[PDB]
Image (cartoon, rainbow over all chains, first blue to last red; front, side):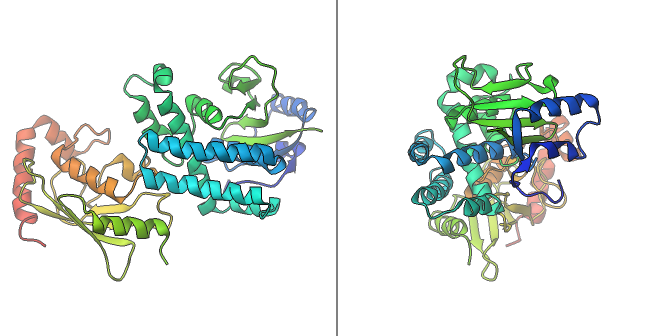
Length: 238
Length: 150
């Protein structure tokens, strides 16, 4: 991971097997072969403690780049999270800075001033990219705090929901656990399918895991691939 | 020039100081703060004035301020280099927090020494097993190092 950008360019799915960290097995080969019948491309996301948040924000921004109507709604909901942070007692001005930065970025996409290329440059600039990522940590924490009664059962014996957020969600470089993953996706109002290279890693014990657990027939709008140390964005063949 | 975030924090710190704490930027390096914390009333550090240095690295607020005690202090969370065992200075820093949060947290530690911090050390072990002796030592160190300084 020495050389790797925060957000890679699109690569053909077949090149996934060229990565040296993959298990050397016919089992891995076979699963990748199966997936290659469905998925045509893969976009690598830097596999650090921010990876899951980053893969989701990339997937979301890609949707917005193709749909201004969705982008308008997402800007409005991001503005409303800004209000909600203040209501839930988040430090006002420090948190508002991150909200304002992310919203200004989205507004510039919406205006048409940013090209696709300009957006991918911003998403690869450590400064800008981490400010944007912080907004997603904040709304994940806000969602948990807002629904604290509902999610308290899932928190380890020792702590409150607020403590869990302060320790496991709000800090940068803290890997998202199962609860954080669910909270982010609900907070962002999206629908994600995670494909697993190894079914043992799946929280639902399935080859894929759809979040949120709906039961409703609605296609996921972001698909990720999980391998040890990696969440990468993957794209269905047309 | 400095990021807007640092300019604003500096302005707010100067307009509204934390009670019992002096914090001012260096005139040559605006990322470098000279800090003095009064030993809290009723603590083993009462009567002392404790000098600290605080620095905001280039990546701030994405990483924590760097902080150390310059005045010697006998405390389960302060090591021989002056480094402070506080999770928010390490992996639990969040960009939502600020210099004021750090200053308040360190001051709070002086009032409530935490020897149960998983990171075991000899001073913490003594605060646990022989609190009487540890407090006596903290009081003696306050007189020795924290009184005719500044």
